[PDB]
Image (cartoon, rainbow, N blue to C red; front, side, top):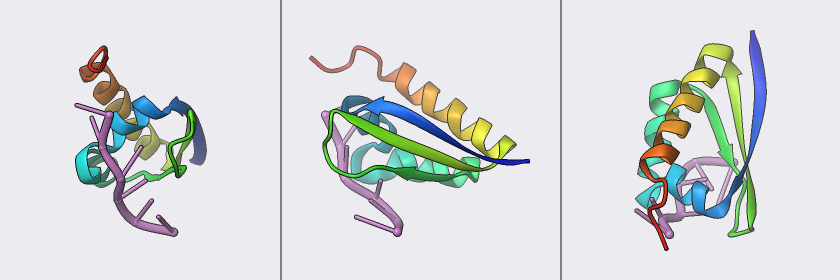
Length: 76
DNA sequence: ACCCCA
């Protein structure tokens, strides 16, 4: 029933997930219940690790993709 | 674009 899932993301996408002052990722952690770790520093690729029961992981993933979708094509 | 918490 508990898993660890790792997402490989570009830095621009991590900016969208984390949000201003971390307000987005703090919301995703609190609402999903997943433990969510994001690798540090402005590297071209970043790793997001989701841990928890599979329903916590699924909700965190849904939130993350919904945030990326809202922010698609938003910076150039 | 957003940079969290460890």
